[PDB]
Image: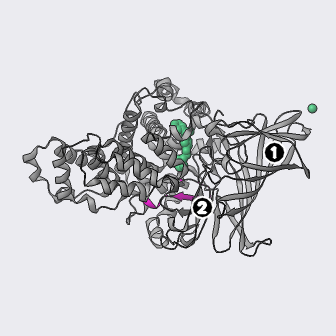
Amino acid sequence: DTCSLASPASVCRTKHLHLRCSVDFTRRTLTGTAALTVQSQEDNLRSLVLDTKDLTIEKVVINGQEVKYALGERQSYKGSPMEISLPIALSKNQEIVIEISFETSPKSSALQWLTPEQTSGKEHPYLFSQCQAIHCRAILPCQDTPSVKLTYTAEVSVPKELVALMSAIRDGETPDPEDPSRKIYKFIQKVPIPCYLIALVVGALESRQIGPRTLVWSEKEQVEKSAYEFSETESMLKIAEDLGGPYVWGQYDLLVLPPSFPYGGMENPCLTFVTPTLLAGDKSLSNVIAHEISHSWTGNLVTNKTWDHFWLNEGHTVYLERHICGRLFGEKFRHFNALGGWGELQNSVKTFGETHPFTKLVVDLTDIDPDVAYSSVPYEKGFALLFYLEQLLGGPEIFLGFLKAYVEKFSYKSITTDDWKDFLYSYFKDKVDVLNQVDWNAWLYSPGLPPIKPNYDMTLTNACIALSQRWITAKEDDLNSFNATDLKDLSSHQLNEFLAQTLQRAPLPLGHIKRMQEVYNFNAINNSEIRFRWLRLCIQSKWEDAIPLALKMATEQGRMKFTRPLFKDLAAFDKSHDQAVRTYQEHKASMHPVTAMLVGKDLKV
Ligand SMILES: O=C(c1ccncc1)c1ccc(OCCN2CCCC2)cc1
Ligand SMILES: [Yb+3]
Ligand SMILES: [Zn+2]
C-alpha cells in the first residue's frame, strides 16, 4: 500500500478500535483515546508503525504503562508516520491493546466544522467526517489502508442538545458523567471494515422512518423533503439483496448533510451520507442511492486492497446500481444510463488527455494524492469493462451469477485486480476461450478510452441526440422553430442527456443559448444535474447573465462534481475570471478542506 506509512498487514493487523472521544466545538478538536487491538503477523515483533496526519499525541499506553513512540517528518498528504516501541516482543498471532491519547487539528483534512450560520437551523454548529480515501489518519492514528479490516466500538461526548451518529449500530446514550452539559453516544460496528469506512456526524439532527430498516437523518428543515425523495430505499435494498445476497449490516440509514458535503454519497456502513443536492422534489437523482446501497456488497464486503484497485469498488457498484435502475424502470433505461456513462468517460479522457496515467483503469498511486487522481474513470471505465464482459459471456442473467458468486467468494476480504481476474477465469472456466479474446493489458493498464465499445440500446437516447443536433446545426434563421413543445416527451433524464450531448460540443453561439433560455426557460429548473450542465453551457458559450447564477451554485453547495468545474469554467471566461478567484478567496476559509485545496489548485492560487 503505497498511500500508507503504517506497518503492512504482513507485519501486524488491527482487529478492533475502541474510540472514546469528545467533540469540542470551541476549539474545533476531537480529543480522546483510540485503543487498537493489534495482532502480530510475525515472530519477535518489537516495533509497529501507524499512519497519522496533523495529530497531537499526548501519550501511548500498553499494559497500564507509558511507552516510547516517535513521529517521523511529514510526507505531505500522507502525513507523519508514528513508530511505537512495544514493551514486550510479540509472537506470531499474539494480540495486544495499544491505547493512544490524541487530539485532532482544526485543519484535519477528514473533517469539516460548521458555524451555526452554515447550517439550516442557524442555532447550532455541526461536524462531519469524510475518511475516504486516506483521511482516517487525520482523525486517529491507524493503519490507514483498506488492506486491513477491523471492528470498532465508540463513545462520543457532545453538547447535550446535539446528536452524534456513526457508521455503526446505535448502542444507547447517557449524560456525560464528567460534564452535565454533555451526552455520551455509544456505537458498535460488529462487521469488520476497512478504516476508510469510519464516519461521524454531530449536529442538531432529527430522524423520520421511511422503511422497515431505514430512518432518514438531517436537520429539522430537510427531513420532510428527504423522506419523500428517498422513499424507494427499501425497495432498492430488496432488489440489491436479490442481486448480491443478504444485507449483513443490520440497518440502512441515510444522513442528509449540509450542502458542503463534497460527494454525491459516501457508503458509510449502516449510515450512508448523501448530498442535499439529491433533493430534486421528484426522486430523479435516486441512481445515487442505488449506488450507495450497492456498496454494501461491492467495496464494503469485498474491498479494494489498495487504492490502485479502486475500480473494483466503483466498477462493480455502478454495474449493480444500473441493474437496480434496470429492474425498477426497465432494460432500455439501464442501456440509457450505461451509454450516458460512456459519454461521461469521453469527457474525463478528453479533460485529462488520452495518454494521462489517471485514465488507466488500474493506476499507480505512488506519490499521488488520491484526491488529485479522483474522477469518473474508475467508475465508467470499470463499468464499461463489466458491461463488455456481460455481452461477451452471454448476458445480464449470466454475468449476475458471477457477480453474486464473486461477492460470496471475497466477502470480508480485501482484493487486487488479479484476485478479481483469477476468480473471473475460474467461474467462467468453460469460457476461457472467450475470455482470452479480451485485450487485458489494454483494458487494465493502457490510458485512454477502452479499446472496444459495448453495444447499447439507443431507444431512449435518440430523441436527445436528435434535439441536440438540431441546436448545433441550426443557423440564425432556424432559431425561430425551437419551441417549448420540443421538451414535451422528455423525462428529466433525457433533458439532462440533451444538455450533456450539447455541452460536449460547447461553445455554441450566444444567440442559440439566449434562444434556448427564451423557449425552454432552463433558468427555472432546480434539478441540480440539469442546472449544472445548463450553467456550464451558458458560461462556455460566453453568456454574461449566467455569471452570477453560476457563482451562486458554485458556492451555495459544494458537491465537487459541480463546484469544481463551475469554478474552472468561470475562471476560463475572461469576464468572470476575476470574480471567480475573488469569490474563491472569500469563501476558502469556510469550505471543506479537500474541496478548498482542489479548487485552489484548479484555479492556480
Ligand atoms: O484511489 C483512488 C483512485 C482515483 C482514480 N483512479 C483510481 C483510483 C481514490 C481517490 C480518491 C478517493 O476519495 C474518496 C472520496 N469519495 C467519497 C465518496 C465518493 C468518492 C477514493 C479513491
Ligand atoms: Yb520467537
Ligand atoms: Zn462509489
Q: Is residue 276 magenta?
A: yes
- Callout 1: SS: strand
Residue at position x 24%, y 46% in the image = 542
Residue at position x 71%, y 75% in the image = 181
The quadrant holding residue 51 is top right
What residue is pinned by disc 1?
38
* Extreme-left residue of the structure: 477
Q: Which residues are magenta?
A: 266-277
Could you classify mark 1 by the number of other residues whose Cα lies within 10 Å: few (under 14), some (14-19), or many (20 or more)?
many
Give the residue type that dot 2 points to. Answer: Leu
Give the residue type that dot 1 points to. Answer: Val
Q: Nearer the viewer, residue 296 or 370?
A: 370
Disc 1 C-beta below 8 A from ligand 2: no
Q: Is residue 64 left or right of residue 254?
A: right
Locate residue 111, reporting x and y percent.
60, 54
Residue 194 visible from this viewpoint: no
Locate residue 10, reporting x and y percent.
76, 34
Distance between mark 1 and mark 2 Cα atoms:
29 Å
Give the mark toward the camera: 1 or 2: 2
Could you classify mark 2 by the number of other residues whose Cα lies within 10 Å: few (under 14), some (14-19), or many (20 or more)?
some
What residue is pinned by disc 2?
127
Q: Nearer the viewer, residue 227 or 244?
A: 227
Q: Is residue 279 above or below residue 181?
A: above
